[PDB]
Amino acid sequence: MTMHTVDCEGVDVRYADHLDGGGSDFGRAYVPFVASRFGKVPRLLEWCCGPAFIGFSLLGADLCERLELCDVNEEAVNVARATVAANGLGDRVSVFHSDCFDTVPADRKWDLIVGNPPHMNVTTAPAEHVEVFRRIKPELVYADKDWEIHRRFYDQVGDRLTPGGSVLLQECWAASDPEVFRPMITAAGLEIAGTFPCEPPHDLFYFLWVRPAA
Ligand SMILES: Nc1ncnc2c1ncn2[C@@H]1O[C@H](CSCC[C@H](N)C(=O)O)[C@@H](O)[C@H]1O
């Protein structure tokens, strides 16, 4: 109910706790990594954006010319727009309410697609895991039962990438590893170009660099 702000690379990002997925903490890993391995990209998209701590920080550090944001939760889309307006970022940001890419403008393609998705397949996750989040966080924040959100995403993302565009997801060692996603990446016509464990103090997390296969 109450709106807070947290500075994400100069952007005052508006959020509510129950929409917070950790992007203002371990999502901070994104700026140094993207700045070393990609430099500034013209068109960046943050999937599963929520309040877009990650996106706004990439924008705020001048790692993208345009930043676009999309999430399935309409409350997330609206809090994200609020942040656009309160930071005067209207000319450089677009927010889309969509389940993965189902209702994202059909023309839209990106050079880099980042994202802090629901991290855990609650079907197979350890009991101790699921219970820690069932009592703390809305199910939309953490739960990808049978990895189905991931599967729709990877199946759709091929046609959403500009020539030479890549995907760079931030995942959780506790709930997955690269091999878990390899079959759905290969099926979709993509490949794992790299796995980069995040450095301390976010080494619970790793980046997955995916891109269309040869
Ligand atoms: N099918 C789907 N399509 C788009 N977004 C989805 C989705 N399923 C879940 N999400 C969103 O994905 C986010 C994962 S939690 C991550 C929140 C935010 N990016 C942060 O770093 O804090 C949630 O906001 C959830 O609403």
Image (cartoon, rainbow, N blue to C red):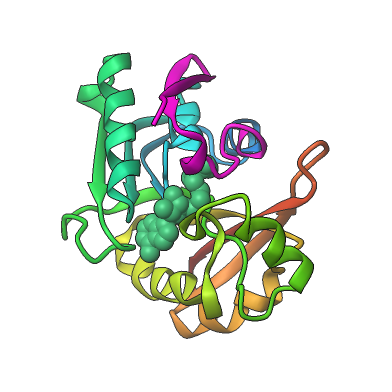
Magenta span of residues: 1-28
- Image coordinates for residue 207, horizontal then vertical, percent: 65, 53
Q: Is residue 115 above or below residue 148?
A: above
Q: What residue is rendered at 78% in x and 50% in y? A: 204
Tell me if residue 64 comes above or below residue 70 in the rendering. Answer: above
Say whether residue 19 is magenta.
yes
Determine the residue positioned at 19% across, 61% down: 103
- Furthest-right residue in this view: 200
The x and y percentages for residue 66 are: 31, 33
Above or below: residue 183 compared with residue 190: below
* Residue at the spot 55% in from the left edge and 72% down from the top edge: 191
Rendering coords of residue 167 (x, y %): 49, 56
Q: Quadrant of residue 76?
A: top left
* Residue at the left extreme of this rendering: 106
Residue 62 part of the magenta-drawn span: no
The residue closer to the viewer here, 131 or 10, is 131
Residue shown at the point (67%, 39%) measured from the top left: 26
On the image, which quarter does residue 82 sit in?
A: top left
In the picture, the quarter occupied by the N terminus is top left
